Length: 184
Length: 118
Length: 289
Image 1 (tube, rainbow over the protein chains, first blue to last red):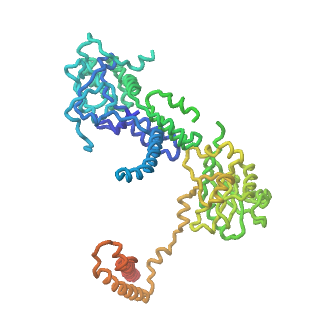
Image 2 (cartoon, each protein chain N blue to C red):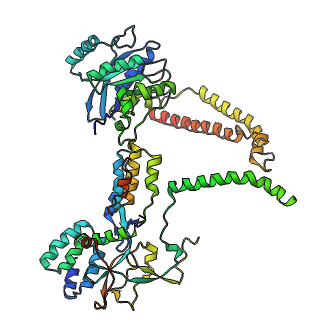
Image 3 (cartoon, helix red, strand yellow):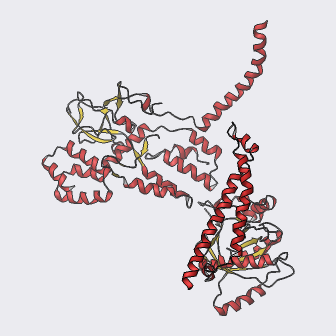
């Protein structure tokens, strides 16, 4: 659902993500037995910055300033697909024929009678925690120092779970529970 | 690895120790993860750290992410019906592979239920 | 739910292949028939180790041309020699047609199906092969029932396969009636490859044989004279040739059937040979005496 990206290696330690590689070799081979195709699944890795409020293991809702250009990291659309295309195409075919069958006669007598990268603009915009966040966009993210939620040590500048210390526990924080809690 | 966690036994703030735990699991090999948890158990290290290094926290966290933020096309359902035939072995497979990747990491049964004849 | 109904990749050994081109091609126009001897392993790997020609018959190929009397008799001879292995199918040759089964050859297939359910029917067209190995295909029955209830997809589950496409009438007849085709593959050992090329001592003995010197003279004379003729034409090529549009140039200066290029080719062949000729003669003279 447009939320995963495939990681080649761990970029933080400069060392192979093992699980991914084994996925890809097994994926290539599929001429022989098509269900080898499913091993592409294991290479998917999700990408998001996820704050963790204390050691409670709950996700705070808070936001971070991101100096970037919005258009760049607009959340990719819902596609048209083939179904949407048929409807839209056939609508155009109708109109197009009709048009010219009337326009030609009417007109005569009418009168007579880039930067792959655009940085992220210096403009700030707030990005919610635990949303789909591109690798490039993650760089600009900086935790708000006024705000209660600050990482124990400075932000990686990359997607992944980063644990925050909460200055005030007194002040209720809006929370999104983990899934295990929902089922009970 | 063990020695690092002996340093933070003394410098034990659970916010700091946990953070370092997340970084480690993303990076390191499963084989390492196994050997480390046995050793730390006998260290009698903090059982908070032990939980992360199992990898179960991270799993839940990513499931909530995928539920909330999935964006699905309705056009896959219809495309599958129209062009492709779920009887033919090649054609039936391609759809399963594309759909499987689509709804990944989250239970989804909308597709199953709708393309139930297919 | 039910059966895959899978069709074997028919693994044809080189020895079997060579007897098929020999007996069939030579025997044109009269058709020839015979059994295939092999071993069946897996559910997709049939190794056809050997073939033989069953004694000719004037009914050519028919249900009754083939016989158990012939089958048994031949088997018994090979039985003693310990080279006996189970019948994995039957071949016959169509020298006048492409690869497909007559209405009759299906009936013939049907008796061998009852014998062994992995029985193949292989139609060999050898005269209208220009590489030998091409236009020979292996087949297996599919029931009349199978076509109705749609059991053609199952057989090729999870495999790219080859479904043959030559002959449009005769093929589509075969594809939707006579039989289902899947890929046919040739395998051989690297002991045998050595035998097929054949090493000889006369490959190298011919390299120290010094052919007569009348023949060196002729080559010297000839090659040089020839390039004198196309060297006039070359002068013509480059007289102007620098005005626009490349196509225009190639018709006017006759750069079609290129004279520059032909000069180079004649030059290279002779140049190469005259160097072999000095090289052999020098080796011969000291080495002997």
